[PDB]
Image (spheres, rainbow, N blue to C red):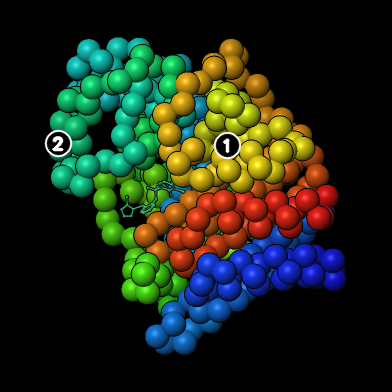
Amino acid sequence: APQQINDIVHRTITPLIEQQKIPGMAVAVIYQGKPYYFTWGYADIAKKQPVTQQTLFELGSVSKTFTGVLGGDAIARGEIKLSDPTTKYWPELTAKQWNGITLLHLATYTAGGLPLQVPDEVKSSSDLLRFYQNWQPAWAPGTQRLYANSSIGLFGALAVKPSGLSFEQAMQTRVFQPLKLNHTWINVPPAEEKNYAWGYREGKAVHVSPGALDAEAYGVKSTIEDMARWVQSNLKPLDINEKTLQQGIQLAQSRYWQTGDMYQGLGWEMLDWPVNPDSIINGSDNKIALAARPVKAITPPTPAVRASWVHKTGATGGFGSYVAFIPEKELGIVMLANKNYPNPARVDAAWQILNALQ
Ligand SMILES: Cn1cnnc1Sc1ccccc1NS(=O)(=O)c1cccc(Cl)c1O
């Protein structure tokens, strides 16, 4: 690790860990295409297990970038189209409010007010059908963005239906395996449980619990090394040998909607680089990121812009993650922590690091 990288990373992350009381953290910087790794603290405070480059963290909503790319791969395979009605893949969805709601709307949170969470009362699949049938939009499709697991989660589930594969099976065979993400899991296998960090919420060790559409919206667990490889793959999609996957990655970074200075991709969110750091820092506060905001359609979508800050924040009850990269600079960062700490602290740290290296 070049001393410049070592210095900027430690000078930024050390105070962050102290200020936020983060039990364990892993960081990867991608600089001129090569990864550099940093670890601090504890994956398991009780058993005194350190964070290592093999520790698994819950990605929370960074999982949506995998769902977005898997959907993009399905488009590239010709199995689905973003301009297809939701009811083409779920014929049982007969309620008339679904007329005009497309897979694009589901993938980009623009269906008209689908809620942030699937109600915990929904367990069975007939519960899920009932929930979506009875849901009443607040807005017409394609007019307002409201960040929602019930939106992109349904997209992920529907996008794999023509393949006949389960969501987890599709993700493993079409995304994880081709990219050699061999320590990235929807369900952590017994063989890897020793590497699975505990999350910490108010001092209690916690793991994410099962829920409806959890795999599609917030269910991936990964190591810092696999996540660095995920960033490298999205920084340089053309190096990828599987044709539909290379195409799907590009599709997930296309710009479909604009609100303020942010653009909505499939999972990924993008801003023009150079960014105003106060825009992404304040913009990452959940108060703005989770608010209902009017969108302007980008007709047709802009293909992946190299001069972009591309990023996604993620959280679970016990974890906080952040990924960001700049394709034009060959530059990227991954931050994984086993405490959910405020988003603006994440983006501030990441911008301080990448700004110093560009
Ligand atoms: C649903 N559920 C049940 N058990 N665990 C979960 S996930 C979870 C739990 C607690 C906080 C955040 C999440 N993740 S989230 O809903 O996707 C999300 C919302 C808003 C912002 C982000 Cl950055 C984000 O990740």
Q: Residue at x 54, y 17 (%)?
A: 296
Crowd tier of the residue under label 2, counting other residues whose Cα lies within 10 Å: few below 14, some 14–19, many 20 or above: few
Q: Nearer the viewer, mark 1 or mark 2?
A: 1
Q: CA distance from mark 1 to mark 2?
A: 32 Å
Which residue has dot 1 on it?
Answer: 269
Instruction: Tell me where residue 156 appears, x and y as whole percent.
Output: 39, 37
Q: Nearer the viewer, residue 159 or 242?
A: 159
Q: Horizontally, is 177 left or right of 326 in the view?
A: left
Q: Amino acid at mark 2?
A: Ser
Q: Nearer the viewer, residue 80 or 138?
A: 138
Which residue has dot 2 on it?
Answer: 126
Q: Horizontally, is 121 left or right of 202 in the view?
A: left
Q: State which quarter of the image contains the N terminus.
A: bottom right
Q: Amino acid at mark 1?
A: Glu
Q: Nearer the viewer, residue 281 or 337?
A: 281
Q: Horizontally, is 184 left or right of 193 in the view?
A: right
